[PDB]
Length: 330
Ligand code: NA
Image (cartoon, rainbow, N blue to C red; front, side, top):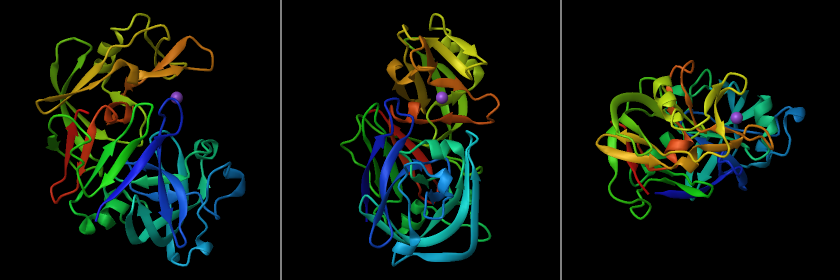
């Protein structure tokens, strides 16, 4: 089997991407944030505290003939941005892009933090990191990908995120029409439960490539590219008037600037992030200070190849017995 679903930016900045997901019988379609940096499929629901729901579509298990309470199971998750959610668990039928899993754990939120309530466009998350990170207790649950894997034509999914445009998540196949040149594969460590890999270096603009190992995670649920402070300083030093602002919480730059590209290494291959991808617009409405899309990972404890980096590539998440990542230009 295979599945193929379109993923759409939630706003004009590509802050996140939503993908429609069918849950239950008859189908309830919710727009979920597919997150390769976490391992819970959780939704706004009929159980969510009413004051914490503001425009989201909810899952109502009582209206699904295939929903079953997973008795005694609870979940609670905290993300890198400080957001959180928690609740109880149902099993139900879940379909993505025509690919169906029966008996998927659907984590129903009883509580969500303010950042979730305030984002009316995101109805929940679908985690695509390794199932070792799943937070369900006392019986840990599998991701949608792990439950689908054995049925797929190939044990893979691909992320093809758009710049200010829709893109695609495919399950079970490589679309050889969706990228240019060849795919370069690189090793993955699953020791922290992430799609963790090592970039071979970077370049700023038309500058020389610096060969250096940068360990980090491929995380579709993170907006920006978070890299070591040395690398980030080298990038922003090429933008007149850019500075790190403790008040704003990262590097800012004059909205009048033209940003340089940023290149990262994947083995001997190179992915180029155009400068425009690194512009996250005014820090507040009408400001002439703009927020940068490359930020320091210092204090986060890991480097994160978030959407700024991933949307410059066609990315293969190879879930074979020995997982690997693949990157191609597009
Ligand atoms: Na922000």
